[PDB]
Image 1 (cartoon, chains in turn brown, red):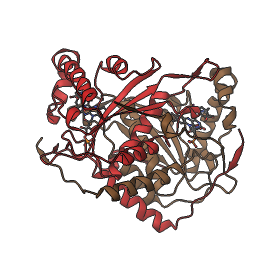
Image 2 (cartoon, chains in turn orange, yellow):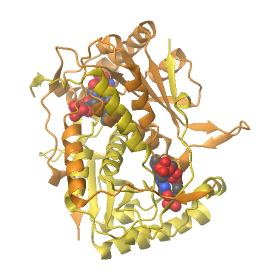
Image 3 (tube, chains in turn yellow, orange):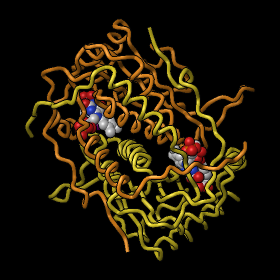
Image 4 (cartoon, helix red, strand yellow):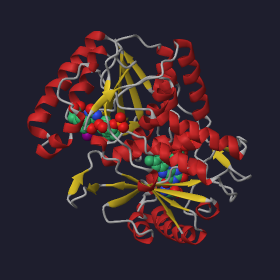
Length: 220
Length: 220
Ligand SMILES: Cc1cc2nc3c(=O)[nH]c(=O)nc-3n(C[C@H](O)[C@H](O)[C@H](O)COP(=O)(O)O)c2cc1C
Ligand SMILES: Cc1cc2nc3c(=O)[nH]c(=O)nc-3n(C[C@H](O)[C@H](O)[C@H](O)COP(=O)(O)O)c2cc1C
Ligand SMILES: N[C@@H](Cc1ccc(O)c(I)c1)C(=O)O
Ligand SMILES: N[C@@H](Cc1ccc(O)c(I)c1)C(=O)O
């Protein structure tokens, strides 16, 4: 493969500060929203939002991500049955006292109404390896990190397009959800995002983010 | 902690589509750039771009990320020695034939001039656990996925601010770099981004991203 010159849009120092400031204020309004309206969302916003995720870097240019988008209420309800079943066992037994205590501030439990109400579910699967045209396995270097980076870009895109979601990681729901949606064995579910508008009764925990001097360290 | 109403941001469906289209076109221009000018960048843009990263979701709201920013020519050079030294061993022995063959199309080698030329290096450390005020360890659920999500948001923010970078994972360099920059034992380096304007003669591999129908699957 050939190498080509890199073409860049140069911004004046003042334009950069402004764009960077606005983008921060924009994304800082993003909250994980666990209460989602059933009102339909324009499918072109979803398409672009996933196109964008696919612009993520990936280890050795492997693109090890599958974004499975579920619209069908029937399928969605089967997903809800599975996750609620496993989460109940997760809260009652598998996560442990410490974890369950650490979640009190979020008031979450194994009841997940948004899996039904949200018009759209995005299930993100990592490809723990891939296949070339000849059918031999190609290695997916840092696939979990690559897909997660892509999930970050997906989250920014949803915020930018004015939709809401919550990044969820349903423990022990992977194999079952994989089988239900007909995904191949080399795919493993990494996380699930319900996407839509906030329902009228939406709340969030009153969480505070660290001040800059607590996430950033400058060295001299 | 109390729970509060979530404030709905109201967009017309069409403005939403327009925003989603523009954001895709913006991020699709992002490329990993391994040739970086030494032209200084405004530290406020860095501050904002890192603020943005800190708005990322995190498992049970743990915010397990430390963004170390290195400006100092001297420290940067010590980092360069470390990474070039280890990458040489990586290409010659530790990565293996297949991996080295897989990197040919990128024309990368163990020489990393950008580590000196770039005005700023951002080293992203995951906190594999934390400490409460009482000195007991708190658990950082999915810290690596969380930090990676933050890095994704970071990459978008840099792209939006007209800065460039390449997402790097310097094999076996974590411990030496941790000690060099005086980071506590609960921090582990996840990746390194050289940040700045692209140098004049910068190139990129002519890579193609998958079409939408190859990363997205819709279900009924
Ligand atoms: C890796 C990861 C996994 C998460 N899993 C869940 C989950 O299973 N359920 C849930 O309600 N939220 C989950 N979240 C969302 C966090 O609880 C949320 O980000 C955190 O409470 C901070 O709130 P905020 O997103 O509004 O800033 C997850 C976040 C991350 C980064
Ligand atoms: C987890 C991860 C690790 C990476 N590590 C390196 C690295 O060590 N060196 C490097 O030159 N590029 C690294 N990259 C960048 C990829 O090589 C690059 O994203 C890929 O070739 C596609 O190019 P693009 O980002 O311009 O689309 C990494 C990317 C990811 C997601
Ligand atoms: N990290 C080494 C080698 C390398 C290069 C590109 C890439 O996508 C991956 I995964 C590894 C380096 O920096 O050269
Ligand atoms: N996944 C379960 C429990 C849960 C909830 C929030 C959170 O940040 C984490 I890490 C785990 C659920 O969805 O309830």
